[PDB]
Image (cartoon, coloured by chain):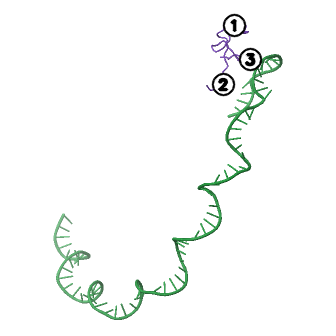
DNA sequence: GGATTACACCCAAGACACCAGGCACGAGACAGAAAAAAACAACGAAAACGGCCACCACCCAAACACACCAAACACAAGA
């Protein structure tokens, strides 16, 4: 399995680690339940792709 | 073919080259070019055979004449 690179992950998508959590664990992970995702985190900065 | 398309002000966010073939030096091989020799042209010397004048005799050319034929004024005919 040659490592060919790292692909940034869209938050609240099927590959995010915040997809399987419930509201309780979300609270423990410092995540706002109102936050809907849809953006990326690059160097700690939230980025959104404009259509 | 270029060149220009409002004015002022505020804030945030990322990068501030990395990596790959050419110059120098680093050494071989046919080609860019140089040296030589052997079959290429000619000329000097000897050999004898082809070329020139005689001698020569038979075959073609000219003269004589034959009969034969082509031809040209004109007496006659003719429209």
Mark 1 in CB contact with mark 2 (< 8 angstroms): no
- Of callouts 3 and 1, the N-terminal one: 1
Palette colour of chain B: green
Residue B36 in the image, given as x and y percentages of width and height: 61, 69
Residue A5 in the image, given as x and y percentages of width and height: 66, 24
The residue tagged 3 is: A45
- Residue at x 66% of width, y 8% of height: A21
> The residue marked by circle 2 belongs to what chain?
A
Q: Crowding at label 1, few (<14), some or many (≥20) Cα neighbours within 10 Å? A: few
- Of callouts 3 and 2, the N-terminal one: 2
- Residue at x 74% of width, y 17% of height: A45
Same chain, marks 1 and 2? yes
Residue B30 in the image, given as x and y percentages of width and height: 59, 56
Q: Where is residue B15, by image quadrant? A: top right
Same chain, marks 3 and 1? yes
The residue tagged 1 is: A25
The residue tagged 2 is: A5
Front-most of B60 and B67? B60
What separation in Å lies between label 3 and label 2 (alpha carbons)? 20 Å
Answer yes or no: is residue A45 visible.
yes
Q: Secondary structure at mark 3?
A: strand
Tell me the quarter of the image containing the N terminus of chain A: top right
Q: Secondary structure at mark 2?
A: loop
Same chain, marks 3 and 2? yes
């Amino acid at each position: 399995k040659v490592h060919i690179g790292k692909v940034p992950i869209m938050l609240r998508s099927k590959f995010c680690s915040l997809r399987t959590l419930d509201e309780v664990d979300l609270y423990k992970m410092k995540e706002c339940p109102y936050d809907m995702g849809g953006y990326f985190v690059i160097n700690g900065s939230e980025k959104v792709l404009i259509a």
